[PDB]
C-alpha cells in the first residue's frame, strides 16, 4: 500500500494466443473485377504474439489454374513487452528455472516495473494465494532485462505460466501466458529398505557430463556474501568452451570490481557491457570459459550485495554446459540455509505440495480478545480444535516434527479421534525457531480439514498460513498476577465454546 | 562468408559477417560462438582449432579467420584430395539476457 | 635427431614439427662447417643426413 500508481494485476490482460501457425483459410473471389482483378479485403484479428507474420497463399481458379503468391509481411509489436523463454521437456516434481525477458524499445525513456510471477497451485513457487511475489525493476531505454524464476512443476502435462508486468507513471501493461509439457520420472527407488511400511492399507482387491559443487558462504567485514562454485569434466580429454548462466538471489548483485578482477583472470572472459552493466538492476550474469578440465577441481568465488531488503529470497541458480550442447546441461540452485538451494515442499509416494507460505496465522496483533478468537474458531473452515501437550520432537533438515498428545476432542470435524491419542504435527525447518516451542508444554491448537497429511490411519498434521497454535501452561503456571490476562481469556474461550458449542 | 566458396589463395583467409535479428523487426545485441567443419560427401570432419568467441554489435558483426591460423590446422598440407570438400559453419549466439539461445549453420 | 627419429609418427597430431626440424638443420648446414671437434662433426652430420 506504499504507492497507489500502478495497474492492478487483476486488470492485466495478458498475451494469450501463441499459435505456431494459423489462418488455414479458404476464401472466394466474388468481387466485381476492375482491370481484370477482383479485390478482396478480409478484416481479421492480430494474435497476441509479437513477430512478423508471414502470409502464404495460392489462387486455384479452374480457368487460369493455380498461382502461388508473393508472401505478405505484417510487422507486429508494442513499445514495451515481454517474451518468456522456457524449456520443453520438464519433469514433474523437480525444481527448475525459467527466464523472463522484458524488452524496452522506447528510445529515450527509462521505465520502472513491478512484475509479479503469478500464483499457480500446479507449481511450487514463492507466490502463495495471498502472499504476492512482486519484483520492482528499472529499464534503460532500448534495453531488456533477464529475470529468473525457480519453481517446481507439481503436476503433469500442459501447464501454463503467467507473469504480469505493470509500470509506474506511464501507460501500458503486458502479460505472458505460455504452456509447455510436464512429465513424470517413476523411479521412487532411492535406497529403500526391504520393508519400510511404504505400502498403503486399502489398495488391492542429471549432470552426466559435469561435476558441479556450488556453495554460497558469508563475508567477514548492506549484506554481502560469497558465491563459491567448483567444477570439472568427466571424460578422457579436456573439454571445449563451457558456459555458466548465473542468476541473482532476489535483489542481489556481484562486486563490480572483483568481477573486473576475475575477468582478466586466466582462461576466462566476460565482455565489457555485461561487465560494466549498471548496479540498478544487474541481475543475471553470463560467464564464458575457454575450456574446462577433466582432471581436478577448478573453483571460483566472488561477492554479492543486497540491493533491496526483502525477508524472503529466491534461490540463486547456476547452469553450466558445453558451448555446443545445452541439453546435456547441469543446474544447481543455491541458498545459504536451504541445502542445495531447494524450496521447501512436502512429499509422499509420488505427490508433493508446496510448503512455503507463512508459518502460522500472524501473532502479536493488538487484538487478542475472545471476540476475534472465537470468530477464527467459529468459522466453518475450522475442522478441528485440539488441546494437547508437546510430547515428542523429531528435528531434521527438511522439517521439524512435534508429537502432540490429544487428551480431549474439543471439536472433531472430518476426523475420527480417540481419547488419549498421539498424533504427528509438522512445521517446516524455516519456521522452527520463530515458533519458540518447547516440549512438555500444553498446546491448544486448531486447523482445517484440508490441513491433514496422509490418509487414514497413517496420517499427519501440517501447520500452515492459517493454522493457529498457542501454548497452554499448567495450573501452577497460570496463578501469576502477570499471567492473569492470558489464562482469563483461555478459561472464557473454553467454557463459552464448551457450553454453547459452536453456534452452527 | 564474403564469397560463397573458399578461395585457396585468399591471403585474407576468410572474413564473415554475422547478421542476428529478432523476428518482430529489431536488431540483437550479444555474443557469438563460431565453429566450422568440413564435409566429404556424407563424411564430415570437425575443425576444432578454429572456434572463435566473438562479440555482437548492434545487430551487426565481423569476424576474421586469418590465413595463418587457417593453414596450421590442415592435416595433409596441400593436395588434389582437398578439392571436392565443402565447409559448414555452426553458430551459437547468446543474448545479453543469458536466456535465449540460437543454433545457426551455413553449409555447403 | 630425437625429433626426426620419431618422424612420420607425430605428423597427424602436431603439424608444427617439420618446421623445428628444418630450421634447426638449416642452422646446422650454414653453421656446420665452422666446428673444431669431431663429436659435433659426427652428430650434426647425421641430422643433415
Ligand atoms: C534421493 O535421495 C536424496 C537423499 O539421499 C534426496 O536428496 C533425493 O531427493 C532423492 N531422490 C529421489 C528421486 O527420491
Image (cartoon, rainbow, N blue to C red):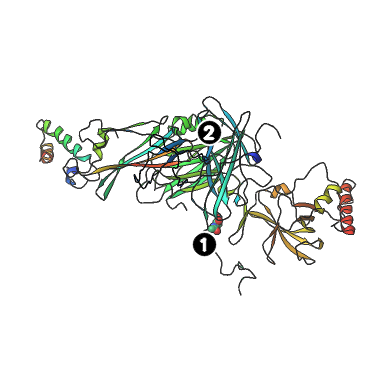
Front-most of residues A332 and C38: A332
Q: CA distance from mark 1 to mark 2?
A: 46 Å
Secondary structure type for disc 1: loop
- Residue depicted at x 86% and y 49%: A370
Q: Is residue A29 visible?
A: yes
Q: Measured from the top left, where is residue B80 in percent x and y?
A: 16, 43
Look at mark 1 in the image and give the residue it sits on: A187
Report the chain holding disc 2: A
Counting residues from the N terminus, which is met first, the one under dot 1 or under dot 2?
2
Look at mark 2 in the image and give the residue it sits on: A78
Q: Is residue A266 visible?
A: no
| Residue A259 in the figure: left or right of residue A460 | left
- Residue depicted at x 39% and y 45%: A293
Q: Measured from the top left, where is residue A335 in percent x and y?
A: 58, 45
| Residue A474 in the figure: left or right of residue A92 | right
Indicate which quadrant contains ligand 1: bottom right
Q: Is residue C2 above or below residue A446?
A: above
Front-most of residues A271 and A203: A203
Q: Measured from the top left, where is residue A395 in percent x and y?
A: 67, 55
Q: Are marks 1 and 2 on the same chain?
A: yes
User: What quarter of the picture does the C terminus of chain A occupy?
Assistant: bottom right
Q: Is mark 1 within 8 Å of ligand 1?
A: yes
Mark nearest the camera among 1 and 2 is 2
Q: Residues within 10 Å of mark 1 (few under 14, many from 20)?
A: few
Q: Residues within 10 Å of mark 2 (few under 14, many from 20)?
A: some
Amino acid at each position: 500500500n506504499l504507492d497507489e500508481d500502478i495497474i492492478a494485476e487483476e486488470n492485466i490482460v495478458s498475451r494469450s494466443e501463441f499459435p505456431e501457425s494459423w489462418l488455414w483459410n479458404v476464401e472466394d473471389l466474388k468481387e466485381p473485377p476492375k482491370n481484370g482483378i477482383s479485390t478482396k479485403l478480409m478484416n481479421i484479428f492480430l494474435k497476441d504474439s509479437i513477430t512478423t507474420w508471414e502470409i502464404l497463399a495460392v489462387s486455384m481458379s479452374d480457368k487460369k489454374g493455380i498461382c502461388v503468391a508473393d508472401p505478405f509481411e505484417v510487422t507486429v509489436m508494442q513499445d514495451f513487452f515481454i517474451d518468456l523463454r522456457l524449456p520443453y521437456s520438464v519433469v514433474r516434481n523437480e525444481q527448475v528455472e525459467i527466464r523472463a525477458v522484458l524488452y524496452n524499445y522506447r528510445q529515450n525513456q527509462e521505465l520502472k516495473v513491478r512484475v509479479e510471477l503469478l500464483h499457480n497451485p500446479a507449481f511450487c513457487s514463492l507466490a502463495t494465494t495471498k502472499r504476492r511475489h512482486q519484483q520492482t525493476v528499472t529499464i534503460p531505454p532500448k534495453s531488456s532485462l533477464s529475470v529468473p524464476y525457480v519453481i517446481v512443476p507439481l503436476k503433469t502435462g500442459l501447464q501454463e505460466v503467467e507473469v504480469k508486468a505493470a509500470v509506474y507513471h506511464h501507460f501500458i501493461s503486458d502479460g505472458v501466458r505460455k504452456s509447455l509439457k510436464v512429465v513424470p520420472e517413476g523411479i521412487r527407488m532411492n535406497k529403500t529398505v526391504a520393508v519400510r511400511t511404504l505400502d498403503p492399507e486399502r489398495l488391492g482387491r542429471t549432470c552426466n557430463k559435469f561435476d558441479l559443487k556450488v556453495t554460497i558462504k558469508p563475508a567477514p567485514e548492506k549484506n554481502t556474501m560469497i558465491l563459491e562454485i567448483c567444477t570439472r569434466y568427466r571424460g578422457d580429454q579436456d573439454a571445449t568452451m563451457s558456459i555458466l548462466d548465473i542468476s541473482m538471489m532476489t535483489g542481489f548483485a556481484p562486486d563490480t570490481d572483483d568481477l573486473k578482477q576475475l575477468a582478466n583472470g586466466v582462461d576466462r572472459y566476460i565482455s565489457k557491457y555485461e561487465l560494466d552493466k549498471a548496479f540498478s538492476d544487474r541481475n543475471t550474469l553470463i560467464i564464458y570459459l575457454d575450456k574446462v578440465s577433466h582432471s581436478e577441481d577448478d573453483c571460483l568465488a566472488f561477492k554479492v550485495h543486497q540491493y533491496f531488503n526483502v525477508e524472503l529470497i529466491q534461490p540463486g541458480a547456476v547452469k553450466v554446459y558445453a558451448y555446443y550442447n545445452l541439453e546435456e546441461s547441469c543446474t544447481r540452485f543455491y541458498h545459504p540455509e536451504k541445502e542445495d538451494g531447494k524450496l521447501n515442499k512436502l512429499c509422499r509416494d509420488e505427490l508433493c505440495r508446496c510448503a512455503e507460505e507463512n508459518c502460522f496465522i500472524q501473532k502479536s496483533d493488538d487484538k487478542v480478545t475472545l471476540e476475534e478468537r472465537l470468530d477464527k474458531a467459529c468459522e466453518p473452515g475450522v475442522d478441528y480444535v485440539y488441546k494437547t501437550r508437546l510430547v515428542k520432537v523429531q528435528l531434521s533438515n527438511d522439517f521439524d516434527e512435534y508429537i502432540m498428545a490429544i487428551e480431549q476432542t474439543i471439536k472433531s470435524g472430518s476426523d475420527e479421534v480417540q481419547v488419549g491419542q498421539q498424533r504427528t504435527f509438522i512445521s517446516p525447518i524455516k519456521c522452527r525457531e520463530a515458533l519458540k516451542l518447547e516440549e512438555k508444554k500444553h498446546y491448544l491448537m486448531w486447523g482445517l480439514s484440508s490441513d491433514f497429511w496422509g490418509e487414514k490411519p497413517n496420517l499427519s498434521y501440517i501447520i500452515g498460513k492459517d493454522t493457529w497454535v498457542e501454548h497452554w501452561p499448567e495450573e501452577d503456571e497460570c496463578q501469576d498476577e502477570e499471567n492473569q490476562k492470558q489464562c482469563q481469556d483461555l478459561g472464557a474461550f473454553t467454557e463459552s465454546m464448551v457450553v454453547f458449542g459452536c453456534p452452527n | 562468408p564474403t564469397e560463397k566458396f573458399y578461395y585457396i589463395y585468399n591471403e585474407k583467409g576468410l572474413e564473415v559477417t554475422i547478421t542476428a535479428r529478432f523476428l518482430y523487426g529489431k536488431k540483437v545485441e550479444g555474443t557469438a560462438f563460431v565453429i566450422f567443419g568440413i564435409q566429404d560427401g556424407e563424411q564430415r570432419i570437425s575443425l576444432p582449432e578454429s572456434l572463435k568467441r566473438i562479440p555482437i554489435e548492434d545487430g551487426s558483426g565481423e569476424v576474421v579467420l586469418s590465413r595463418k591460423v587457417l593453414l596450421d590446422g590442415v592435416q595433409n598440407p596441400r593436395a588434389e584430395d582437398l578439392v571436392g570438400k565443402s565447409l559448414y559453419v555452426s553458430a551459437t549466439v547468446i543474448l545479453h539476457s543469458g536466456s535465449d539461445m540460437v543454433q545457426a549453420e551455413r553449409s555447403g | 635427431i630425437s625429433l626426426q627419429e620419431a618422424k612420420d609418427i607425430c605428423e597427424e597430431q602436431v603439424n608444427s614439427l617439420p618446421g623445428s626440424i628444418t630450421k634447426a638443420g638449416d642452422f646446422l648446414e650454414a653453421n656446420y662447417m665452422n666446428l673444431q671437434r669431431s663429436y659435433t662433426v659426427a652428430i650434426a652430420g647425421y641430422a643433415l643426413a
